[PDB]
Length: 250
Length: 58
Ligand SMILES: Nc1nc2ccccc2[nH]1
Ligand SMILES: Nc1nc2ccccc2[nH]1
Ligand SMILES: Nc1nc2ccccc2[nH]1
Ligand SMILES: Nc1nc2ccccc2[nH]1
Ligand SMILES: [Ca+2]
Ligand SMILES: [Cl-]
Ligand SMILES: [Cl-]
Image (cartoon, rainbow over all chains, first blue to last red):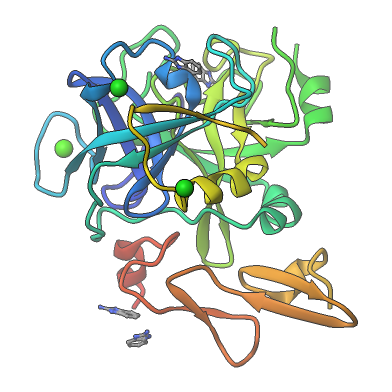
């Protein structure tokens, strides 16, 4: 995250850190005790699928304080329409091997109904994006979890204000075009979380952009509302052998 | 009332029904109050709420 602040410990309790062989991979969002939503592109270069770990309750990466909970990722589910190396359909549903324990520091973000998300949440101007990604374009990643408030643009206005992949109906833009404030590499897969009448909801996934905080460009986010029914159906399904699963979309 | 305007007055989710009928619903871990619109937590850790802040104003 570029131009944000530290998320005070316990104030981003749905935030997930994904690790591969102990190394930082991506962020993700907890949506109940065994399910995490992330970005499909996070897994384009995984070689050993059995070394993916999800960490909940994480805040400061330089210390252990006992609120952290690690879990093996048993399944990575990606829609059939996603093509590795590309931007569209950038979503993954991750099944943890064992539930996390909900605590003051570990709490799921609500996955909203589609209509509610489309008719109501989509018009809430500002939302929060978070992660341990780069603090600057071409710079070091964060040791403490950062968060940033960003405004959402209608796609017509994003295209008009920007100055290369399309912005499809499975995406939306959010942030600033003055180079001050953005999500960045390493924040990929993390939450874009929207507040409505006292509760927070998952509306986007940190997905892509032209560099980070590039003047004349906005951050791009996977439009989660398009995937609600797809997600809900997979969460009611029985696990299958083999970590990676491609599932038909729609 | 209709769900496309002002969320049907619902705090959370809204269904339109045949006629001038609307039903509000709440996410798992919440229940709908007798006002027909508000949602109250039924568990310690409902989704989308931040315990340290909820306690900070309890
Ligand atoms: N690593 C990886 N990620 C994929 C997503 C879709 C199809 C094949 C894939 N291989
Ligand atoms: N805005 C934005 N989001 C990103 C996600 C991954 C890499 C670079 C990015 N820039
Ligand atoms: N389901 C439920 N709702 C409650 C409200 C107050 C105290 C305990 C409760 N358990
Ligand atoms: N500990 C505890 N249990 C609860 C059940 C419902 C609402 C609030 C609650 N706090
Ligand atoms: Ca720590
Ligand atoms: Cl099944
Ligand atoms: Cl495998």
